Image 1 (spheres, protein in one colour):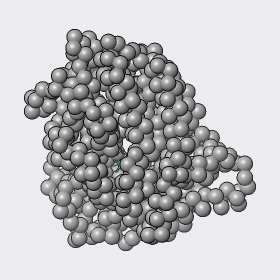
Image 2 (image 1 turned 45 degrees about the horizontal axis):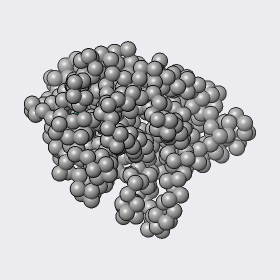
Image 3 (image 1 turned 90 degrees about the horizontal axis):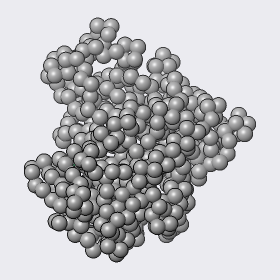
Length: 524
Ligand SMILES: Cc1cc2nc3c(=O)[nH]c(=O)nc-3n(C[C@H](O)[C@H](O)[C@H](O)COP(=O)(O)OP(=O)(O)OC[C@H]3O[C@@H](n4cnc5c(N)ncnc54)[C@H](O)[C@@H]3O)c2cc1C
């Protein structure tokens, strides 16, 4: 056996997994990533305007109190270069890179039932054995594309936001962006003032609220650092872990004037989860409440965008649901003389040619640069790109052919000694706290197994199915089921997130570890 544990991924999840298993459990560990450096999604996504949804002081690890006191809190939210710099400092400080093998994709992982360990094979045909396999593959996968006809004929710059190259310049160029979601809102806002002309190809108009990303004073920062213990206690006692005052107030239980005041206060403070969950307690649950949130944003759109026909084209016709978006000046962009909005739901893209995007009306939109601002695949995307075989050689893709599943978001029946970080049916909450929660639970179970000579840990089918039912029962009280959210698993009816909150999740998994790991088979 080469290692006690093998870790796939060197983002937030894989890095803390390595720290806990190597330095706290004193195990022999190796992590692998295709990336050339740590950071995960913050290494891969380097597009213009990439920015956290979580406020800076909470989008980080909490377990190293020296790091908390040391860390840079430059603005209220944190840019992609600065998240990457942070994670590199973590790897510096805890000497992680010597046990990470970079530029190394994992092709397959086959469980050896005779030896109760995993046979792991890299894409360069290196074989490694390890008792435990930690799959820290992240909650999102890159989504490829149904090829637009003729895309291969385009002779200008063709950039995908999931593989954004260095050295891109914008001045003097006609630029187009396909995609107006999470990523597209950030890219469009960042580049509109830099290009000669911007054409935005909008397939679905989405809601977005201001992010309110401001510089943090030394005073601001000192008071956060003085109160950090209480700040994290509030995280662990919350549903979402975003530092919000999570509301229980029903939207329709106050007057129209008081409702507008509450929305306006959130709009001015900024933040997508703030607008959706600090204002009232039923926006994601009650359609009448949700329409109030919709209308507030639609009214802001009509006030910001002066041309009422442009404002109409930007105005959504859907539920205010899915992961809430925020922006640094998105609707304002459409007042610019050098910006054109194309509704490609009404006027679809039908072809790309050597110098243009062609819409169904026959119009050739001439471009020097075309940007595909893509969405993301759900969690199981990264898993079916690895040939993972468990008991009886059944693959993870086959085991999940009828929909992904898990016990607690961390274990899959028929896949012993494998632990997922951010696997299917993990809570919806701020990611670093979820990740620390899961990594610490896995390490407690693994350290337990080492102390009790147990060498095969497996969730039962009944435990997996009960968790699917638990998640289904919560998720179907909400509008997220009805809203068809790609990042929650609508393209895999079902929402593959535990939506009972971080505090309740930590109660659920602590009950399991406290009751002799019920739902798990512990074998010697
Ligand atoms: C632009 C953007 C902004 C975000 N902002 C927020 C935010 O504000 N708040 C929040 O809570 N979440 C946010 N997220 C969600 C984000 O996924 C998490 O916060 C967190 O970064 C996930 O870390 P991870 O280590 O779990 O996964 P990742 O960072 O995705 O790391 C997974 C790693 O696994 C590697 N890997 C996968 N398959 C293989 C293989 N076969 N072989 C080798 N390596 C492999 C990948 O290369 C990747 O580096 C954001 C995501 C994006 C894309």
